[PDB]
Image (cartoon, rainbow, N blue to C red; front, side, top):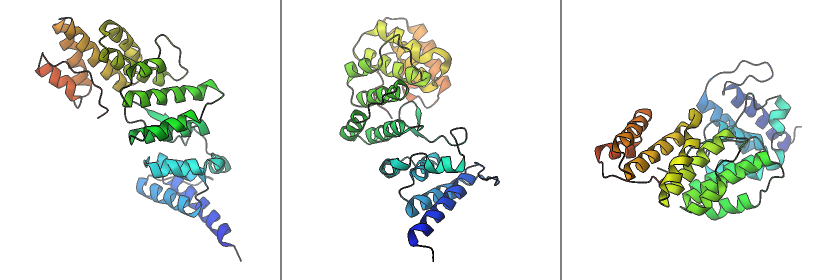
Length: 274
């Protein structure tokens, strides 16, 4: 006579396995498939039957659902962070859930502290800045690798509330980051902050860190666009046009570049996420 908790727990583990399989992840020597909607349903089933299984919430992120309910479900279950993937032998090599910060990057959830960062990023995308900041405040990793993500998402928070000096404090020039992408996107936000403050020459220079290596193309676009505005500001119109066409060609949906090409008087620093 299996108890109800035991039946729920076993069913949740099997739903987890099925979701992973439907995500192209082989488990226990079973053949995977590619059924994204089934994967999401399976992971949702797992969280309904065992809401204490943190990795099932994380799996719903992998499957595309980064709503606040999912992030908050994962955070409530954080005690079992990693238990079920470890039980299955599943690693970051196969299973790397991420959340978009809504501006430049997908942030990988690899630890309790990076889950907190991702949750704060999602909070801040919903304009719940107070809760985001509290969550970052209460995080304080002892190891510098995860603290870089805290600094970055605090910068995103400052960027989203147009606090330009605070943005600059989060992303100082000539600073080594263990995460190259955090540095690149941070530089795009610093470039935007500097341009907004009218410090055009420094904006131009900071932009290069967002451009180098095309590591984060969306950061590079913002940076190249902002360099075009700087060039336009000092009357170097032909060079401005080169960079603006470069960006429009890189990303035809980058409407401000088209606007600036259509209107040589257009002079907008892009502060809106959009």
